[PDB]
Amino acid sequence: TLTYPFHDWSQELSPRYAQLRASDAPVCPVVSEGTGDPLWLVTRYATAVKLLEDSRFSSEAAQASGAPRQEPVELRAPGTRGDAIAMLREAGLRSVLADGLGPRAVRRHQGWINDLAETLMSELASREGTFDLAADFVEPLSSALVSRTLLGELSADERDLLAHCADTGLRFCGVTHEEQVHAFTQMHEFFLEHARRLAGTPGEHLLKLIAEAPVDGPLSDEALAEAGSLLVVAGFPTSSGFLCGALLTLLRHPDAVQELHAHPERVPSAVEELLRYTPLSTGSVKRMATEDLEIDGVRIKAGEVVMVSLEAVNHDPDAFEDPDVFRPGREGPMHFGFGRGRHFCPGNRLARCVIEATVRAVARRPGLRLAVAPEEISWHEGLFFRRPRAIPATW
Ligand code: HEM
Ligand SMILES: O=C1N[C@@H](Cc2c[nH]c3ccccc23)C(=O)N2CCC[C@@H]12
Ligand SMILES: O=C1N[C@@H](Cc2c[nH]c3ccccc23)C(=O)N2CCC[C@@H]12
Ligand SMILES: [Ca+2]
Ligand code: NA
């Protein structure tokens, strides 16, 4: 009877996750609030590893039109496929995706990324009074990441349109179903008109590499538009949400920032602890059983969908000692912030790059603090990917 999700839109995780984790079942039944579909939910690290490393639990089947789902509307423009990353790997573009997202891309971009983080923070430090870290730091940094490494250079109006589409479509509630569907239509139509132009501009952004890649015909306009929409939904609200949330974590732990100021070699460990500690998605990764399967004794029938809450797994006390403590350099198992298994985040190298640049910018300037109490922060309610409306801050 427990409905999903748990409406924990701020950084305070729903107590339900710890309740289910401690129950006498390794997988617990829930019901989608948005569709009424029955779903399974996993909250334990050990069980999550077993699920996400078993390829008979399929991500593509759980994404497909008509699957039991946690979200109220399908995450695709009506009439399109909506399985972009599979379509691209299918067309044989794994080598291309690695070139635009892997370590070689990080080496191309890390210089200007760190310059931009410093320039943005330096500007804020020159101001008298308070400022807004979301509007004045995260938005320009995440927008530059999307323009320069993924899509090609966007105007402010185009960036605002894509941001609004992502915020409207990637929601559990707070907008009508038809508004949500039309957000995906608008984004698809944007790239039908503009993807070729964006791919043709100078630079090495991923969309250009995709459009220029030989495919055993070259990618059609619809396929390139689905690639554009993928890069927005997977890269934009995730990066902006996480950087906002990571800044809040740092601002609430001045002792840890002071340690990083004195010992910059410890920043990479802080990046990894932020990926474990800072909650991002309010939903779960999910997979469909492609046949009758068993998870730690519980029978999962073919066609049923099993969810894993990455936040729940990242706060599992059997995996991490004192899991609700922000402890850079804790020496436990690998976090689940980027997932697990074959679908591990391919953006993880660029994400780590921008997170590291942000942590270093903060650590160089101790004294940065929230200008309001954490409880006074206002949160966007119903987003898949948590984000505060503003982060008032000052030195
Ligand atoms: C440029 C930035 C990013 C890009 C281009 C990107 C891209 C992608 C793509 C294309 C996928 C789909 C993989 C698949 O289904 O096989 C994915 C998955 C994922 N991403 Fe990223 N991502 C970015 C940033 C982030 C950030 C900041 C996080 C922070 C937690 C994140 C967490 C994840 C997770 C957990 C998954 C796994 C989903 C699953 O297992 O079903 N991503 N990413
Ligand atoms: O490439 C995908 N992977 C999975 C997980 C996911 C990864 N990033 C996401 C962002 C929003 C929703 C889901 C995801 C998915 O549900 N997908 C629909 C939109 C993108 C597609
Ligand atoms: O909230 C969601 N999370 C992703 C998985 C994910 C979990 N954590 C993530 C972090 C970044 C990207 C994707 C994820 C997913 O598959 N969804 C389908 C409907 C809602 C949406
Ligand atoms: Ca169905
Ligand atoms: Na798999």
Image (cartoon, rainbow, N blue to C red):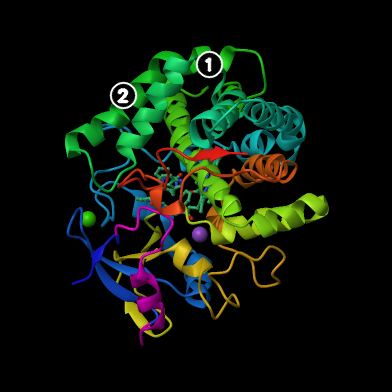
Q: Residue at horizontal 51%, vertical 48%?
A: 245
Q: Quadrant of residue 223?
A: top left
Residue 392 x/y as whole percent: 49, 39
Q: Residue at horizontal 55%, vertical 61%?
A: 277
Q: Residue at horizontal 60%, vertical 12%?
A: 201
Answer above or below: position of 184 versus 380: above
Front residue of this view, candidates 357 and 27: 357
Q: Which residue is mark 1?
A: 198
Query: Which quarter of the image is occupied by the N terminus?
Result: bottom left
Answer above or below: position of 137 versus 16: above
**Kind of residue sitting beneath label 1:** Leu
Secondary element at image label 2: helix
Query: Which quarter of the image is occupied by the C terminus?
Result: top right
Q: Magenta region: which residues?
A: 7-25
Apparent side of residue 109 relative to residue 286 in the rendered image (left or right): right
Gap between marks 1 and 2, in whole Å? 17 Å
Answer above or below: position of 332 versus 242: below
Of mark 1 and mark 2, the one earlier in the sequence is 2
Apparent side of residue 144 relative to residue 294 in the rendered image (left or right): right
Residue 121 x/y as whole percent: 66, 32
Q: Which residue is mark 2?
A: 186
Q: Quadrant of residue 194?
A: top left
Residue 225: tell me if it is visible.
Answer: yes
Residue 179 x/y as whole percent: 21, 32
Mark 2, Cα crowd under 10 Å, few <14 / some 14-19 / many 20+, is some
